[PDB]
Length: 218
Ligand SMILES: O=P(O)(O)O[C@@H]1O[C@H](CO)[C@@H](O)[C@H](O)[C@H]1O
Ligand code: BEF
Ligand SMILES: [Mg+2]
Ligand code: NA
Ligand code: NA
Image (tube, rainbow, N blue to C red; front, side):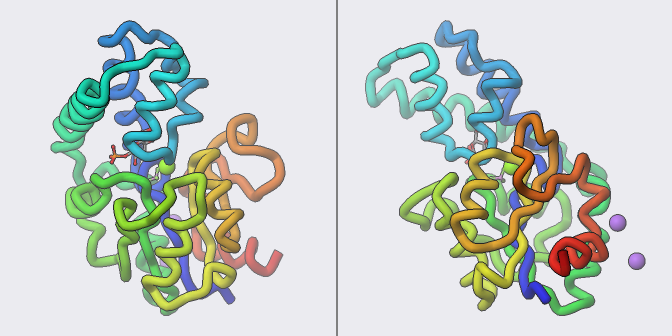
């Protein structure tokens, strides 16, 4: 049986992928880049703050100074952090709280494997911190998603091999990171976005311990 579940945060635990999208789009448009639409944003889900800004600048083949790059990333983060102040337990996605409870009852470790430096704050907003055995700090890894490092780190932090773990993700970059870690990915979203080569569920209510078992048994 699997011994850990490695949770992405944004778009898996709660709807904060939507807020990242809205904040990046606002930022892009301030600098005259209009290509950050929902389709493009699939390339930003699960990607670090700095890598995200760089992808936006590349979309338009735009160079900015190092000083401006720093200011832009800070501006978007400040906006995003204001947006999320009112996140509460009511914003936890369906099925997620009950999954955490069921995992703990079955002695399955729970680790966060988010690309976001805002992860700990969000878990606190949602009263979820006590469910997590570890949080892999995305600032500690040498390589961010789609590199597997964050998922490997999350597994190691709870004393479990990646190959005995399930990873839950909503993003192209994160699915690739899970694959390359050795963990088993179960995506949430559209196969049109995430691929037809892993198990994908349409919404998080499908993330039950019963289903994770159904999938692991195969
Ligand atoms: O700015 P943060 O909260 O540190 O982090 C990151 O930026 C990306 C922007 O695309 C999001 O998609 C990530 O999921 C979120 O971790
Ligand atoms: F979207 Be995850 F929190 F990197
Ligand atoms: Mg995500
Ligand atoms: Na449930
Ligand atoms: Na139950």
